[PDB]
Image: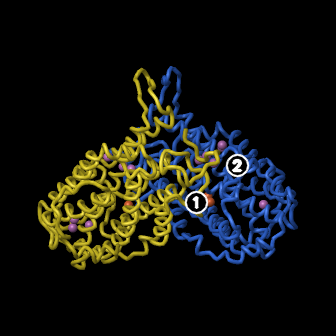
Chain colours: A yellow, B blue
């Protein structure tokens, strides 16, 4: 029920962001919500090439670092590599099949494309600070701790994709597949979408930022400055990605785009609160692990867990969820020097 | 069965290009086929912004243009806009879910992305030469000839996507869905992907270059210089895209990748040939519409057909197919200057 070019003439300004008629013509002269055109323009103006960044002196730095500090650094780099590996492909695979307005379609493709640049940057860093990159890469997939913190990310995406396939194939209704009954509900799919967007928002809004803090702590000590420069470019991209999902979510819950989604958001609002808190919880558990055999000069588990709570409150506030933590001021205002956004 | 991050630690170097274990880690320190890494690097080095190109004079040139020359130019532009609209999303929706090596995955996403830039360049051009671009964009969907010339593109993609979904949901075998039998054969799926690739190769190798010739015809007459700069940047990208599909296809037929693909490429040779022949015939028939209000000096149906046969022969020989047309020299050698 999906087509790469819907032959029906439709007003793209009147379609919902999702589940409407698949986008046929890709035009940018007009838009239902110009936030997406704006984001595309900004992301294109930020285009950068990891290769052009010199990380030459990061090798001696990483080598001179205390063992436990190497752990903190490489562990964080590995998780970041995981995040962008998924973000490079997922928005395309998961969202393109459901988008019904061209600006959002293009935004998603541009967003995903920018994530592949991020992935490319990590290979650039790893290659210049370690002799055998394979060691690093072949420890991301099985790393028990990394799967633990990354828990739930792929699942949300995968269930959305599966429901989407059933929806496009069988359509709305009650069906039979090899003796088993399979119910396909649009309302359920919409919920799956919403939960998935919330999860991606938490990924780019908090998970990425916690890793930035870990990375810039070294930059503060004039260490791993090659990596620092690259992470600064990535955080600038992430600021945009974050804005994109916040708008998607706020537009979906406000009821202007799809009344039914507005209803759905309200009722699973508590589920969303829980998934957000769980994400922050995983970040905390990770922190506890990062500094088990040694804290870092300028960043320890305590300060880091404070930051998680601090940014979590802000992000959740931005998408209409209650604040789970105690309000406080930024525990690490020095981070602002590196977050040009 | 599809996952955005497969938990199995696998040797990405031993996976086949398609249908293997979905890619988990996106690494670029190694590759089974360095050709895709090379294509990514080159495409990234070619990054350009459409709007950055000055198309100010084009409005005047276009307005001053004879009415039938406007039609030729715009009809060509509308088709190009359609191809890039499809090529911006399709490679990602149809191929991404089936790729099993990182370099190819990122290449497809980079390739698809470069297409949205092409699409954006058309909006840039349109919005700058006509008072209301909505009068151009709207007809793209309903224009019968357009739908007739591009006929068959979305079909291949859509059929591949549907079969892929059945595969990821049910896996191989003979299943029962709503009291009906649905067979899911991986071999049959490989055939679909293979013919889909051959078809994209025909689109970017022939359909695109035919449109370039029309655009550049005006360039030689010192008209629409802004459009030509843009078309000259697009063609540069497209040369990488076609190089990319030619390599996917040739690598599959070599047997060096998935053995079954090599056999399938062998069994489907006539289909191969037939779709190139048909795509060529469609380009010719489009001429009858492109020159309804009359042709122009240096660009007519006769020359269009000659070019089509000429370029098709070259493209088909590049992927090991027999040449259907009589041999001939380039009917428009002046295009070589704009193609680089
Ligand atoms: Fe990223
Ligand atoms: Fe991101
Ligand atoms: Fe293109
Ligand atoms: Fe292309
Ligand atoms: Hg999502
Ligand atoms: Hg998700
Ligand atoms: Hg750190
Ligand atoms: Hg941190
Ligand atoms: Hg780090
Ligand atoms: Hg929710
Ligand atoms: Hg295709
Ligand atoms: Hg294809
Ligand atoms: Hg195609
Ligand atoms: Hg032509
Ligand atoms: Hg063939
Ligand atoms: Hg073929």
Q: CA distance from mark 2 to mark 1?
A: 22 Å
Res B88 → quadrant: bottom right
Residue at 59% of width from left, 72% of height from top? B51
Do marks 2 and 1 share a subunit?
A: yes
Point out which mark residue B9 bears.
Answer: none
Q: Which numbered disc flags the more N-terminal residue, 2 or 1?
A: 1
Seen from the viewer's position, the closer of residues B218 and B339 is B218
What residue appears at the point 86 percent right and 59 percent down from the top-left corner?
Answer: B293
Q: In the image, is residue A172 above or below residue A65?
A: above
**What is the quadrant of the N terminus of chain B in the image?**
top left
Foreground mark, 2 or 1?
2
Q: Specify whether B274 is left or right of B251.
A: right
Residue depicted at 78% across the width and 55% down the height = B308
Q: Is residue B287 left or right of residue A234?
A: right
Q: Nearer the viewer, residue A38 or A238?
A: A38
Residue that label 2 marks: B142
Label 2 crowd bin: few (<14), some (14–19), many (20+), radius 10 Å: few
Relative side of A174 to B130, left or right: left
Query: Residue A122: percent from the left, percent from the top?
Result: 36, 64
Residue A62 visible in the snapshot: yes
Residue at 41 percent across and 70 percent down: it is A50
> How far across and how far down the image is residue B152, in percent?
68, 44
Image coords of residue A118 (percent x, y)? 39, 64
Q: Which residue is mark 1?
A: B115
Q: Which quadrant does the C terminus of chain B fall into?
A: bottom right
Q: Secondary structure at mark 2?
A: helix
Return the residue nearer the eye: B206 or A283.
Answer: A283
Q: Residues within 10 Å of mark 1 (few under 14, many from 20)?
A: many
Q: Nearer the viewer, residue B225 or A28?
A: A28
Q: Is mark 1 within 8 Å of ligand 3?
A: yes
Q: Position of residue B273 (x, y in %)?
A: 72, 43
């Amino acid at each position: 029920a999906y087509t790469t070019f819907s032959q029906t003439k439709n007003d793209q300004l009147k379609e919902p962001m999702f589940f409407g008629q698949p986008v046929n013509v890709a035009r940018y002269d007009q838009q239902k919500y110009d936030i997406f055109e704006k984001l595309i323009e900004k992301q294109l103006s930020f285009f950068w090439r990891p290769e052009e960044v010199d990380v030459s002196r990061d090798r001696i730095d990483y080598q001179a670092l205390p063992e436990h500090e190497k752990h903190i650094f490489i562990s964080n780099l590995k998780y970041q590599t995981l995040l962008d590996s998924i973000q490079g492909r997922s928005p395309n695979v998961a969202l393109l099949p459901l988008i019904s307005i061209p600006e959002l379609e293009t935004w998603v493709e541009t967003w995903a494309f920018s994530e592949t640049i991020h992935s490319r940057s990590f290979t650039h860093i790893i290659r210049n600070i370690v002799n055998d990159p394979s060691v690093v890469f072949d420890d991301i997939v099985t790393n028990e701790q990394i799967q633990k913190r990354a828990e739930g990310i792929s699942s949300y995406y995968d269930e959305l994709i599966e429901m989407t396939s059933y929806w496009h194939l069988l359509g709305e209704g009650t069906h039979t597949v090899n003796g088993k009954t399979v119910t396909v509900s649009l309302r359920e799919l919409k919920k799956k979408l919403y939960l998935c967007l919330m999860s991606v928002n938490a990924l780019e809004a908090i998970r990425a930022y916690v890793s930035f803090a870990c990375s810039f702590a070294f930059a503060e000590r004039e260490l791993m400055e090659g990596n620092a420069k690259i992470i600064r470019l990535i955080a600038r991209d992430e600021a945009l990605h974050l804005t994109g999902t916040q708008h998607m979510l706020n537009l979906l819950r406000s009821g202007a785009d799809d009344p039914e989604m507005a209803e759905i958001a309200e009722e699973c609002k508590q589920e969303c609160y829980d998934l957000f808190v769980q994400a922050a919880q995983q970040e905390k558990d990770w922190a506890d692990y990062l500094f088990r055999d040694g804290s870092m000069i300028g960043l320890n588990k305590d300060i880091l867990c404070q930051y998680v709570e601090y940014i979590t409150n802000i992000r959740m506030q931005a998408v209409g969820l209650d604040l789970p933590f105690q309000t406080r001021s930024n525990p690490i205002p020095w981070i602002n020097t590196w977050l040009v956004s």
